[PDB]
Amino acid sequence: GVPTYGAIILDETLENVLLVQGYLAKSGWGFPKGKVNKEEAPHDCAAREVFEETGFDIKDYICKDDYIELRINDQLARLYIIPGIPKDTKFNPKTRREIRNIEWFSIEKLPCHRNDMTPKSKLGLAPNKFFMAIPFIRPLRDWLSRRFG
Ligand SMILES: C1CCCC(Nc2nnc(C3CC3)o2)CC1
Image (cartoon, rainbow, N blue to C red; front, side, top):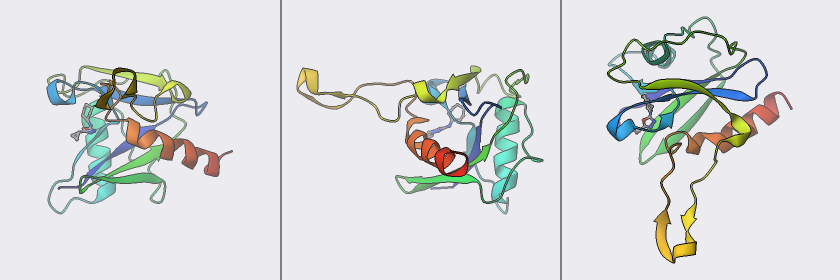
């Protein structure tokens, strides 16, 4: 799969993260991110995708070594960590045909797994609107603990 790049934007308290809501297949909440173009450097793709989806330019704030990266179904997704962004920032997608809404969420309130359906003796996982974000939540919490504590 083609690698994706984006950002985990946190506010000044380190409590809240910025998620964006797409449409259809991307109908839930996730971190801003998208597919790398040919010959495009990871930091440039992250900044482009974030600016397209949020209207906020991270370019002056990217730290090269500060990211969480996951390989899901043999696609690589790397989110640069960008703390300290004020909660009163005006975010506006470029692209309202792609982005429904943009909100801050409390990190401690976000799920770090979906729930099973053990109550119903059925296999699988219950739907959760944070499905696209969830894989990153525990690594994010651990990364923040190590870096700040
Ligand atoms: C809406 C705007 C665009 C970013 C999008 N990010 C995303 N994270 N996982 C996926 C699935 C394709 C694998 O997409 C979700 C939020």
